[PDB]
Image (cartoon, rainbow, N blue to C red; front, side):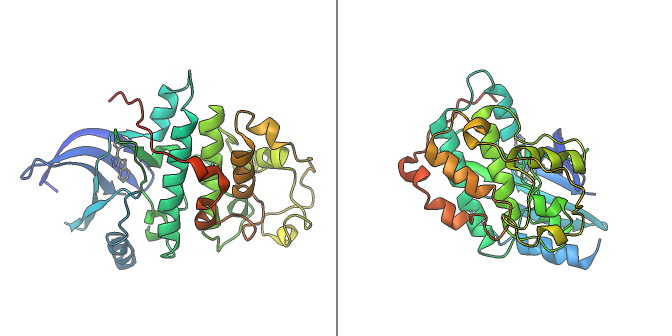
Length: 281
Ligand SMILES: c1ccc2c(c1)Cc1c-2n[nH]c1-c1ccncc1
């Protein structure tokens, strides 16, 4: 809309480009996304406007004009990928990691309770502000409408057509590990490299740990068989409570994977607080 003055491109996705923009008539600063128009898309996106929660980036307006689709979102000041890179030397303080994980699980528990999945969680769509808040962005968009495979759940990689809310828990678990170790957990650069990286760390799944896995669409009996490795080796700095929680977030069987709601009650969050991040914007 000519109702906005584009300041700068704050990113790009496959579902569209995102810009920092100012509302030409109200001076308000926002994140303007021009979607890259079916009625179903319009209806699903319209549903997202009501899905409001303190840990979900607010969708301010939906502008379907001149047969185009623009999404006006609230503008935060930093995404988690940049914050992680900037904190690479010391690493994000554990209390902050815990706070962020707790908040994101609250956001997920909320959307999941409304049957809405994100499907593509990653540091780039997790936005933070100076007050210690972290929020889920660009979600509900996947189902409504190089791509990184690093946070993709194994059931999606094995070809499951109807995945559940568990896919989000898996992605968040990978991000949790990344914040703690300062290295991506499963940095695959292809679908099979991604799958095998997961197998080499958590062990090749079988019917014992994941009933029904061998009949999944893309499963091959020829998959090499790797043994699982201790979480003590995978996320060393993390204490037992965090390790136990992470292990339940990375269960192979989606039905065995912990829910966001249950994760909130895990002992790991017994001492959760809300520290302020060291931001440089
Ligand atoms: C989709 C929907 C809303 C938003 C985004 C993507 C990215 C984004 C969104 N809102 N604010 C920001 C942002 C702020 C500062 N630095 C990077 C990004």
